[PDB]
Image (tube, rainbow, N blue to C red):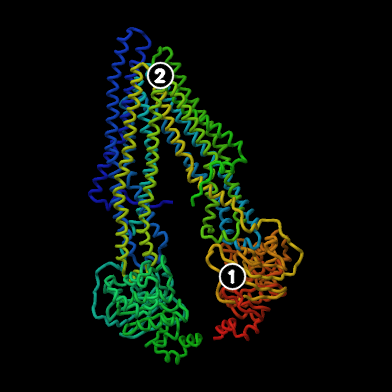
Amino acid sequence: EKKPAVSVLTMFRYAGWLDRLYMLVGTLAAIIHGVALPLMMLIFGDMTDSFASVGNVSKNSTNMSEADKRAMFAKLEEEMTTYAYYYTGIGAGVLIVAYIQVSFWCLAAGRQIHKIRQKFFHAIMNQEIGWFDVHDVGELNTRLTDDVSKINEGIGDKIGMFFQAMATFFGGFIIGFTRGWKLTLVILAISPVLGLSAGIWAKILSSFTDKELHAYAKAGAVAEEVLAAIRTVIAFGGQKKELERYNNNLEEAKRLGIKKAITANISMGAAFLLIYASYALAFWYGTSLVISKEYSIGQVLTVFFSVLIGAFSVGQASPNIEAFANARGAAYEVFKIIDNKPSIDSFSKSGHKPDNIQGNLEFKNIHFSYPSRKEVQILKGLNLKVKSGQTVALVGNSGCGKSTTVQLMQRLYDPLDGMVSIDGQDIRTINVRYLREIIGVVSQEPVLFATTIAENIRYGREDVTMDEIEKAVKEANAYDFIMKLPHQFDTLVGERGAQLSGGQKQRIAIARALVRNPKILLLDQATSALDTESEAVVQAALDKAREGRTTIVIAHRLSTVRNADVIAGFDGGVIVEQGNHDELMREKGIYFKLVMTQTDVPPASFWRILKLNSTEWPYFVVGIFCAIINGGLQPAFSVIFSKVVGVFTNGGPPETQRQNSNLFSLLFLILGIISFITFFLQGFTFGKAGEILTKRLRYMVFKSMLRQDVSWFDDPKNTTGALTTRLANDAAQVKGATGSRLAVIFQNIANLGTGIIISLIYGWQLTLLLLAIVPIIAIAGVVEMKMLSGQALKDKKELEGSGKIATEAIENFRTVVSLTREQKFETMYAQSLQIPYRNAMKKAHVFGITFSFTQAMMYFSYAACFRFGAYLVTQQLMTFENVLLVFSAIVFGAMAVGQVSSFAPDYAKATVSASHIIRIIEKTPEIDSYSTQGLKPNMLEGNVQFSGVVFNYPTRPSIPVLQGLSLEVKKGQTLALVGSSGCGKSTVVQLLERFYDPMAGSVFLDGKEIKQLNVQWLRAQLGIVSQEPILFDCSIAENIAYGDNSRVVSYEEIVRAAKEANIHQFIDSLPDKYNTRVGDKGTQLSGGQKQRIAIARALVRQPHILLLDQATSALDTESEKVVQEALDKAREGRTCIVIAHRLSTIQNADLIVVIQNGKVKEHGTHQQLLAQKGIYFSMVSVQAG
């Protein structure tokens, strides 16, 4: 894959001359700060020479008593005044420089973003409507705030840190070469061995990464299928069969998880070894160059560090490039849109603006193809005139052609041939905005914007008085309902506010269009989406709106049409018949045939989580052990480094300097080996311990999830997706809080513990300073991580309003362009953006300081140590060796916990990720579907009885559905439930299923409380048939046999059921018979066919009760009669409850219940409820008239 990017020099367009200056001045700061630490190493070298030169004089030979004490020691006291003044000089310059660096870079980036957001949005509001047709709008809106957020990374402070790291790369390799070149070319011969070893593992870790996501993708697919189809899963008791499918694919990603877990800790210790190796090689060789009196001890300690800093400076500039290249890439998809210019420019000011429009309309030889499907011609040779003040209705067979006419007169596409003219004038020769200002449009579905009614109306024309609104709302027939709304004209509508009916929204849409006082009216099914009641007021308001306006109406009710002055009949893009109603009727053509048919804050305990991995404590014991050793190797190195430098700085004979130096030099590879061993074993024991824990926890969750009752899966929070996430990554992210947390804390304790102890005895005065100040500098790195994050919320929350505005505008682009308010939303966007602008321009001032005062308290405090430590050698109270054994035992050890803590997984993100897992496991349901107790008799009667049932849904607890609902179905009878639309009718089926218990009342089965019968054996004798039958991606054999689980389904037993479902004959005429894969992968089945399969699945069980809920909810007319045949077969001598919405099934039923407000208003046979002349009578009358 090769994703494009922008040329670097392009991408900084929109950068003003002041931004070109800030980036320059800020860079010069970054270069200075870069070389500023190499100087700290040069002095640190020349400081040990000053100590080494005298450290062995006052000891070895006792020449003078106090004329040697004061001589050498009053020399150091004057030498160290300068080295301390030198150190403090850096921190002063750092404090200034570091501020200018991040100040000026974040500033110049911010100034550029605010100029990008506005230009990018405007670019989107300037596109064509065929431009929106081809593109996916969803990713476009996220591209407004994600891609613009991907650029601000790679132009902000991330550059200032890069030129810093490069200024150290060259600043560091400079000092090494000019102070001694043998040592460096030794090291730079090894750094290719390490630059190679580093990149290799990232190629091998990425290998075992993508292979893992394809391992769980099998398991996580079974997960998604179940939890969408859970209603079918519980109703057929396959809660364990689905646990095994999810499990038998769950071992793949475990074994693969180990090849990542081992090879990750190999990669750690492998490169952790090559540091300890190249340390000895550079010190073994470095000691041999001071023995021959070429270098001093101060020379080596400069050069070895000033290389490794500059050499490690690359790895710190790796991501700052990658973030800059991510910014180039995201900036391409955006800058393309800004530089794209349309043919139909909704912003240009080109064409005429003719006054006194008659509105003669002429279509001439129009040919047209849409641009998403340019292979299909829509119109061929289409011709037609509208005379001033006339109404034109367009009729004809189903097609997009009629609306295409309406879309071309808006000029939202440019026809392929022919010409659309107004008063003799080509519509492509006037201006676009003037055109649409004279044109109103009432679309099929009305868009209301989330504002007040006044503002929704004012979108039509922003200079309007409340008087003028009042006239229009009247004309649209919306005034009386508005006066009855709670805040009248200020009531808030849209997606956020009070819901208006369909009829009321359209009259508002009509009022919006009326304010425009256009000369032409276009209506595209303004009455389709409305029942005959709501429609009458709307037709009256439409009919009002047409007076003296030129009108083309896409009509759905025929009676509305007969008031038109002329009818055009369309067939295949071509006007076949044209005339008044009687002419086309007389023609007995197309038109005639038509008109005579229509007549989350859980704090889990650290110990609770640890117990989850307790089954594998032997893995844990070892990992603790190696976590102590590896935590002890750091204070070892602080000695073996000190004991080396001690030789050359405290006193010794040059007869022992060989064996002491070379010994300690090879104790590094002792330490280096022990590093590699304790890591390969730490991540082999704590590694499997985690990859076990995931697999065992993903199972225990998914098991515990199917145990839950239906009220849980009804919740808004436990949607089928948020459960797959919780089951997939949150289940795995736990292991960063069981073993990996012990490995940290045992290392961290074993590191700072044993290093505090040692430094205290070798000299306690220096330590109480350092362990008092390490608290200070350690704090500072946290508050930066906090306020970098706590500030991330503020600026990025204030952007949601700015982003929500744009969301409202893109999601209804076809609407707003017809209102020509592309500019209004642009202004609304910019004004909202002025807050995160002014906040960000103070932000860089802050992070300028938090970055400045971090480095100043470190460079200053570097003097307060090597000053205090120096006075301890002046006063003959401590040696220079013991200082280095204190300094590099606290500092390099306090630096160790950070290098540990930043590697290990985010502990906070893992605990809360785990606390949710325990809750999803420890939850026990109201309805233990898994249970084993319950009566389960041999009594196959099947008398059903509801007594005074009272029930509310706990998802929607305030609503009543059933109050005192009582009703019996006697053995073998069919009962039909009828009544007004409501969940009361449907609820009876879910309570007999027992997906929920009732709050009060009782459901009995043969005289027995269902709360006392096994949940599995209640549901085992119930065959459910839902509206939309859910089929599993699987063979026909599996989908039908799924109904009777734990059962020996034979070829014989399946086929008799398919006979009685009436599908047998259909199976035998198609390929591969009963083995056919069904779903999206396989032959796609129709709507009608699927339901017939659901009946067959229920038939195999041969249950005593059949539950039919709103079945036949489809339009396949022939299929419908097939279903009813199978159903009459399926009903035979079985106890049946049918939720009937279509009336004809009910006539042959043995008993009918009419339900209203939880209460059984009436009942009887078909004939008896009719002759009562009550509620049932009212419903049935609607069908025949």
Residue 3 in the image, given as x and y percentages of width and height: 40, 52
Mark toward the start of the polypeptide (1 vs 2): 2
| Above or below 700: residue 687 | above
Q: For the point 48% across and 40% down, which residue is it?
A: 904
Q: Secondary structure at mark 2?
A: helix
Give the labeled residue for mark 2. Answer: 646
Residue 815 in the image, given as x and y percentages of width and height: 37, 70
Residue 253 in the image, given as x and y percentages of width and height: 57, 47
Q: Nearer the viewer, mark 1 or mark 2?
A: 1
Q: Residues within 10 Å of mark 2 (few under 14, many from 20)?
A: many
Does the rendering let one see residue 714? yes
| Above or below 540: residue 144 | above
Does the rendering let one see residue 818? no
Point out the residue furthest to the right here.
938
Seen in the image, is 82 located left or right of residue 915? left
Residue 87 in the image, given as x and y percentages of width and height: 30, 28
Q: Which mark is residue 915?
A: none
Q: Nearer the viewer, residue 531 or 141?
A: 531
Give the labeled residue for mark 1. Answer: 962
Point out the residue furthest to the top here.
63
| Above or below 790: residue 748 | above
The part of the image, by quadrant, that contains residue 1089 is bottom right
Q: Residue type at mark 2: give it.
A: Gly
Seen in the image, is 345 located left or right of residue 1065? left
Q: Residue type at mark 1: give it.
A: Leu
Q: Assess whether mark 2 and mark 1 are in contact (beta carbons under 8 angstroms).
A: no
